[PDB]
Image (tube, rainbow, N blue to C red; front, side, top):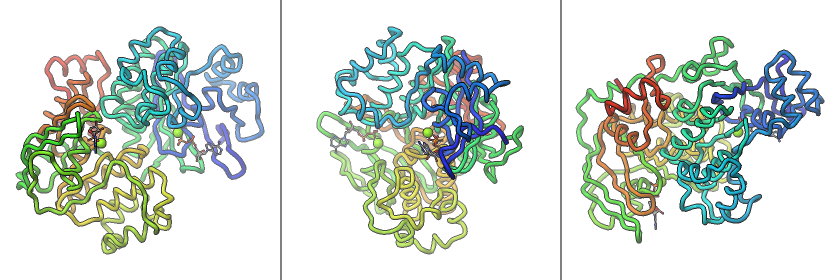
Length: 515
Ligand SMILES: Nc1ncnc2c1ncn2[C@@H]1O[C@H](COP(=O)(O)OP(=O)(O)O)[C@@H](O)[C@H]1O
Ligand SMILES: Nc1ncnc2c1ncn2[C@@H]1O[C@H](COP(=O)(O)OP(=O)(O)O)[C@@H](O)[C@H]1O
Ligand SMILES: [Mg+2]
Ligand SMILES: [Mg+2]
């Protein structure tokens, strides 16, 4: 194999092949972290001269090395400066330590297209313009970075993981704004871990596979549907590569309705006031042995609702009268345990750690066994997320509450967590409520849905748990995106704006198919 593009050093990480870039199209990239996705972006953006796994140190070398490839001309243009790709960086948290002043100052400066007013609208930046960069949240930094990139005038735009820190509405609206670039004839390359967003965004897909931290390989370009389906199946036909020993199928959105579950508990109208913000919860019922997905933009009260159910927060009005044990995986986790992951988890339930079912369905797929000897206080955000999810699912309780388990996880880890939640809840016949912004995770794990509506920071309303179709129709109408079903894998499939299916579904008010 002589498709070696870059080696980080002796025994360091090596990248094989590169994705294609095409004007007028969106090329999506999907794969586990540590496999070279950002490295390819750096190379194509001109930020890193690939050494071709040798000593190459010039663009001329790359130009000769890519003879016979459509990228030869690309690199010629890159070296000559006829193109200067715009890059929305992955590590938006580092923006402050390099930029100062008001957001409106950063954006006016990036504005080379006179679309400031439009981009601000799309990314909900109206109240961030006057804010200083130093006071921005990870979420606001992400949206400001996507806006800066969208405002530039160039031919090539590369977005590295734009959905991180964005709520469900924000990530789908940013995807619409990003895709518009290709409609204007520009070329877009986007790396994404949220499969629904990746789907809606892309015309072409590359799957990246390999061994995290050791090597990564870009697949041949694939049509959007075929690429995402091969990814779920764990097997790339043409390349004849099986990167996962099993398939992840989504077929199972119908049986989760034909079964009369008993009621676990009911809760009455609840109100939680935080100064000027107010959350009103409509009376609801929770069934034994079901999973309720919870969706809604942020700053609306999802976490506040979960906290009241977990008993960590008290309602201002209304009273919950339960005699249930609850296991709770909080949205923001702070490691504070002097001991290893194994010590922490073995103290929760050692019998489950030694259980074949738990090792197969939870510990191995989430990579927990490989973290057993790690000190909890030294875990990264993604490692801590997996360990906290496992810690929560290892507890013995009537109800399990998981507040945003997909944050910090890569696409493969998300699929592993979706399966773990579903399989363990089915096994233990218990109940869970899961707040999530990742549509395919919601789809995979949920039997019913609770939708939150309101004005972020001002007021929120928790609608009672309803069917998947009714809840997604309610949420999606607010965003103008429709999903149908893909028979091959059973996954929800995004319709491009204006397509035949999109028009048909919108006219009928059926924004989300299951059947
Ligand atoms: N500057 C560097 N020096 C050495 N190794 C690096 C450097 N940048 C990235 N790597 C390593 O290369 C691998 C792939 O990195 P990256 O392209 O950022 O992955 P991803 O698919 O998560 O975006 C990782 O194992 C990473 O630690
Ligand atoms: N303890 C608190 N004191 C004051 N305001 C709070 C408190 N907890 C949450 N809030 C505010 O309540 C609103 C709802 O927050 P939250 O429930 O975290 O939202 P989300 O839907 O993003 O999980 C936000 O505007 C938040 O700033
Ligand atoms: Mg990356
Ligand atoms: Mg929250």
